[PDB]
Amino acid sequence: NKFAVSTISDYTEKINNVKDEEVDDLIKNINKYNYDLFNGTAENQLPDYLNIHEGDVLGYIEIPSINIKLPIYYGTSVDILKKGVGVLEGTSLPVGGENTHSVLSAHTGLANQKLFTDIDKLKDGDVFYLHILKKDLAYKVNQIKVVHPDEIDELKISDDKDYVTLLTCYPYGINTERLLVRGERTDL
Figure 1 (tube, rainbow, N blue to C red):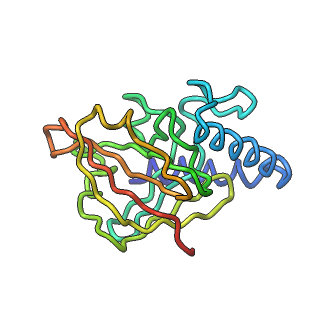
Figure 2: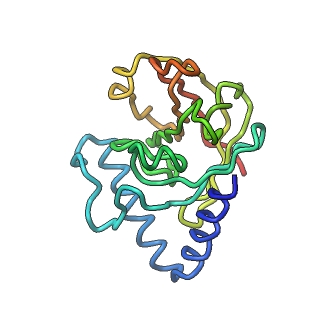
C-alpha cells in the first residue's frame, strides 16, 4: 500500500511547486482537448503542447467505501497497471466538465496489490474523489456495466454529462469481460 503513498507524496510536492497560472494554462489546453475529443476533431495522440506522456502522474483517486487511494497515470500498459490507475487513451482527461467521459483502468486479482479488485463492491450512491492538477472532483456511482472488450472502443461521451468510469477486467481470475463502474459529477 505504501508505494501508492510515496508516488502520491512526490506528485503533491511537484504540483504544489508549479505557479497557479501554469496549472490554469494546462487545464485550459486540456479542456480544449476534451472538447475536440467530444466534437470528433482530436487526433489519436494527445497534443504535444499538453506535455502529458504515457506514465506521467496526473494526481490520484480515493474510493472511500473500499479503502482505495491510488495514483493516476496517463495511459495504459502492463507497467502502469502493475503500479496504479491508467487514463485510457482516447478518453477525456479527468479534469471534469459537461461532455466529458474519462475512463480509469486498473487490475482485479493481481497477487500482492488490490488496485480495482473491490470496485465490483461499488453500488449506486457510492462516491469517489479525483485530485487532478489541484482540482478536487467528486463522482457518485449511478451505473454498473459488464461488457465484451469490443464495447470499450464503442464507449461514448454522453451529451451534457460529466462521467468518470472505473474499468477493470472481470470475472476474477478469468478477465474475459470489462467491469465499468460509472460515476457522475456531484458536489464535493
